[PDB]
Length: 145
Image (cartoon, rainbow, N blue to C red; front, side, top):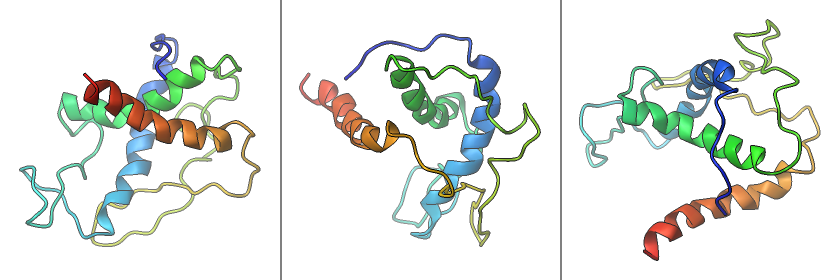
C-alpha cells in the first residue's frame, strides 16, 4: 500500500502538531530504562531518540513528523473526508484537549493522552491492521529489492 504524497495546506497545522506529537510520543521509550545520550548505542543503557522535535537534527527532526505523515498521507489518500474542519485543539484554538494524562519520573515524560472517553470511529479500529501492515509494506519494498 502506497498511494500518494501529501499537499502543503496542512503546513499551518503541521509544526504545532509536531511540537505536540513529540510532547506525546517520546514518553514511550523509557520504561525499559533508556535515557538521552550522544552516540547510538543501547548496551550502555541509553537512547538518543529521547530529545524534542526541534532539538534533534533535521534527519531526526523529520523522524518524529514521519509517523504523523503516515497517519496523514494514507488518510488523505483514503477517499473519506479528513480535511481540517474540526481544528486540532492545541496552540490554534484554546480548548486544551491534547495535554490531559502524564506521569513524570527520572526520564523524558511528556503527556501522551490515552483518550478513551469517546467512541472511536469505525475507520481507525479497522486501520490498526492497515498501519501495522504498512510497516512491513515499507520494509518489503526495500527487502524484496
